[PDB]
Amino acid sequence: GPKFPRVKNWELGSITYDTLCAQSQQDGPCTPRRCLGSLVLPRPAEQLLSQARDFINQYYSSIKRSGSQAHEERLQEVEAEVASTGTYHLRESELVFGAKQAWRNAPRCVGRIQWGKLQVFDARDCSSAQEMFTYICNHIKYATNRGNLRSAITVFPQRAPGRGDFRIWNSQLVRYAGYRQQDGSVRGDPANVEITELCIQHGWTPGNGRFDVLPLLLQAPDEAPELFVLPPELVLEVPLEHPTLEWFAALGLRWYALPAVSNMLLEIGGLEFSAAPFSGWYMSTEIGTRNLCDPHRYNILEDVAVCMDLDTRTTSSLWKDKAAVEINLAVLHSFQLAKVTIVDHHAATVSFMKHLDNEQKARGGCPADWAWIVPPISGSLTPVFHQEMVNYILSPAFRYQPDPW
Amino acid sequence: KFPRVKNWELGSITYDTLCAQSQQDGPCTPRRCLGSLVLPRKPAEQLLSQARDFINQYYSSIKRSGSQAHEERLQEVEAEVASTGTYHLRESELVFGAKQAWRNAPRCVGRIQWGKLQVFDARDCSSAQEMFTYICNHIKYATNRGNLRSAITVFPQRAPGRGDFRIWNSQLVRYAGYRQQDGSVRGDPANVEITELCIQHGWTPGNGRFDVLPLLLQAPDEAPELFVLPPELVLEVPLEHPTLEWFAALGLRWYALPAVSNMLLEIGGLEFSAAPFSGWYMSTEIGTRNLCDPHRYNILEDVAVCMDLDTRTTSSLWKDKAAVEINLAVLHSFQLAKVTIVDHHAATVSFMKHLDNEQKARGGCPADWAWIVPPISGSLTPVFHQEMVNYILSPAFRYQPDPW
Ligand code: HEM
Ligand code: HEM
Ligand SMILES: Cc1cc(N)nc(CCc2cccc(CCc3cc(C)nc(N)c3)n2)c1
Ligand SMILES: Cc1cc(N)nc(CCc2cccc(CCc3cc(C)nc(N)c3)n2)c1
Ligand SMILES: C[C@H](O)[C@H](O)[C@H]1CNc2nc(N)[nH]c(=O)c2N1
Ligand SMILES: C[C@H](O)[C@H](O)[C@H]1CNc2nc(N)[nH]c(=O)c2N1
Ligand SMILES: [Zn+2]
Ligand SMILES: [Zn+2]
């Protein structure tokens, strides 16, 4: 029938067709012979120009002024800037529309119903590492908002031909130290071993606990990274307790409130923003399931299971399933007590379904990656598990970029 | 050309070379991934090469590639197809192909078992009656008093100049679904269509929540025929919880034997439209989907209420707590009953070993991440952290349209 992908919700028996995917200009890793859908990492003037033109059209289209003479003048202006410099600049409003669109387009983000509510800080005037720190602090302050979390993004100056990038070396703005121990093991977050060591190499005196908030290594073009300690009263944290299990608080576990991804590259109409930290609010499973329970992270399942006096000798006692659920409950209860925005995976996925319906009307489709959308506990208990999804790459986009060291 | 395949828990890396043996196209293009689609919307010369390829695979397996016997058999197949437009499999080749199609099923977390499969040759069959006898012997052997054994029974291939042998039921054991006055369903709502078919063709029905359906079996170009399974043939496991006494008051049971009967078996271009197969259950299938899905037995909320859980808000995780307990009732019960079952932790661990065995034997293993990762506690198992390449290899199992 309709010459477009047919997508079905198996739980409601409803069907849709994706026409959005025709607007895709960049290929992913699948072919007709094999799907590489599960791999984490995918893989001059002419090229830039056509990306810019395309972006400008999305912009003018979004303000229902497509085919306008303001529209036309703008296209000319951009293509003049490039023929003489090899690049162009985005006006304020265009940058705001581009960063919202790059979020909206992110296939692995379950939080997109919020896409329209993003507070965009233009730091394209920033010119030093000390100044990057001020912008980042102001970002944390506004985003945190004493627990009532607000989505934000700070956009530092774009990449320029033959000139080093603005970079944030840290993968998030708040990260716990991971200290590799004499005896082979790790204290704190095993995921941050590399970055912790970088900080020490750069003259940070490390602490010694499981939840030591790392300083920031920030880099201005062609200069060495400089080191900044976030003032702890800016870094809001939540000590973890359980609603009925009294001993849980005695575990001494905590998590920070603000999820601020700082390593991704932001692409708008062919322009490339190497430094553009963004934050929203956590889904409980990210903390309660991945950060605390992954075997290669804090790995606490067994310690919790032993406090719950479960039989850890056999898989079939479902000790891992029971301990995980209770860890996730703790996380939710602890944020709600502390009055810090957080969302549970049932609510999140429910809102994602509603987002899917909005986007069908608005654009004809929604690029979505099933394996990242579906939560890491209770998958089939969430409506997104039963929903077929089409994955494809739209621009503007967040991308992974190489570590700058 | 040979994709890199990383495990993110342990950082180990492998390369998949087997993918190049794929001859069938999936749903994906460079433009868009369509790997999450459940089903696809996706002349005698297409056959000859498919048969040649298969006869090669088989001789390769018995280390006689290039023998007199292999070249001899090759020509014989080429002859039979040039004379008749079809051909026949030697039994030991059928045995090999049926295992190979299990081996190649990308969606199956149970493939470490692939080598142990009892194949019944049921190609001497000319009636539904004979179909039924074979099915009863299958079930008996497979169930083996609770100590389950994987098996497949293969019925005669499709022929161009006639209708197929078919088993109408999608599984050999199914719980009836009755349409009630108020529009509600007594029993299992997934089997309403087939319940009504059984009735329409003569069956006098029951009115419990777990009535075992009769079989509708079909020989070529003939009305289907009704066959009641003798109760003692169908091993059932009553459901109870180890610590929660009221669970048993729910009156739940599940059957011991998962026996899929609606799939088409493809071997060297030959098609066996009736070839039912059974293994044993992973506990999540019963404890999560069959009991917890709202379109099925939909017991989640009942169970949570009895757990005394706050059912008003998502954030209490009542759904998550109840499912775990239900899944646990399933394991406990099968273990109490002494019936073979595997939990999702043990199953996904055996699968990780499968991948390693297949890497060494064949240079990879096609796998469907979304189906291999279980439907609860996904990241808790090791397959979650494992990258996977998906592609269609032959021999294969595939879907076919319902015969009505
Ligand atoms: C406000 C609440 C938000 C929630 C609840 C949320 C949730 C999530 C989750 C759970 C993931 C996958 C996480 C993982 O497993 O690593 C994700 C991915 C992602 N999020 Fe959102 N997010 C939110 C806000 C934002 C914002 C403001 C942005 C950017 C403006 C954003 C951009 C992205 C991107 C680009 C990815 C994909 C990462 C990748 O490609 O690997 N998110 N989100
Ligand atoms: C012996 C223990 C076995 C276990 C634990 C097992 C487990 C599973 C599971 C959990 C699925 C997912 C399907 C679903 O969630 O609905 C599956 C799919 C599948 N199984 Fe296995 N299985 C076993 C034996 C077998 C046998 C004996 C065969 C045939 C010889 C087989 C063939 C398949 C095929 C072809 C699929 C894919 C179904 C599809 O395309 O949707 N399995 N299996
Ligand atoms: C805003 C926001 C909201 C929220 N609730 N959670 C997060 C953290 C999860 C996340 C969201 C987006 C991007 C990344 C990390 C990007 C990344 C980069 C590389 C190089 N490898 C990866 N595996 C991941 N992580 C961010
Ligand atoms: C052997 C076996 C072992 C085991 N542990 N679980 C099962 C049940 C799950 C399963 C395994 C293989 C094939 C199918 C049938 C899938 C299907 C397809 C279509 C198109 N409609 C359906 N109703 C069902 N189901 C079977
Ligand atoms: C191998 C697999 O693709 C990889 O581990 C993915 C699976 N799904 C995920 N989903 C989310 N949200 N986050 C993740 O880190 C992952 N990991
Ligand atoms: C739409 C979605 O892909 C679909 O419901 C799949 C997802 N993964 C699954 N995985 C298993 N094991 N069984 C299933 O039925 C499904 N359903
Ligand atoms: Zn794909
Ligand atoms: Zn359903």
Image (cartoon, coloured by chain):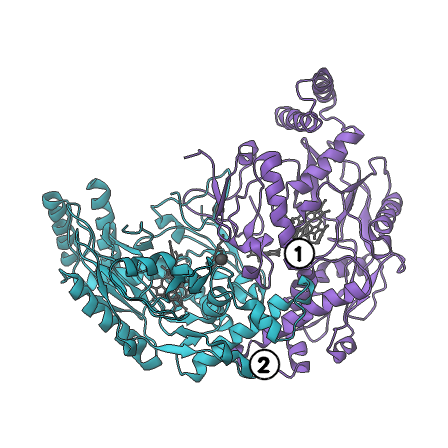
Chain colours: A purple, B cyan
Residue shown at 80%/66% (left/top)? A337
- Name the residue tied to disc 2: A312
Whether residue A39 is visible, yes or no, is: yes
Residue B185 is left or right of residue A222, and the answer is: left
- Name the image quarter holding residue B186: bottom left
Residue drawn at x 17%, y 49% is: B159
Query: Does mark 2's beta carbon lie closer than 8 Å to ligand 2?
Result: no
Using residue B285 as the reference point, say whether residue A67 is left or right of it.
Answer: right
Q: In this view, does A107 lie to the left or right of B275?
A: right
Q: Position of residue A302 (x, y in %)?
A: 64, 77
Does label 1 or label 2 sit earlier along the sequence?
A: 2
> Which-is-in-front pick, marks 1 and 2?
1
Q: Do labels 1 and 2 share a chain?
A: yes
Identity, as a three-letter code, of the amino acid under mark 1: Ala
* Label 1: chain letter: A
The chain identifier of the residue carrying mark 2 reads A
| Callout count | 2
In the image, what residue type sits under mark 2? Thr
Pointer 1 local density, CA inside 10 Å: few below 14, some 14–19, many at least 20: some
Q: In which quarter of the image is residue B181?
A: bottom left
**Secondary structure of residue under mark 1:** helix
Image coordinates for residue A252, horizontal then vertical, percent:
78, 74
Residue A58 image point, x, y percent: 66, 28
SS for tag 2? loop
Residue under label 1, please give it: A347
How far apart, in angstroms, are the residues tagged by discs 1 and 2? 31 Å
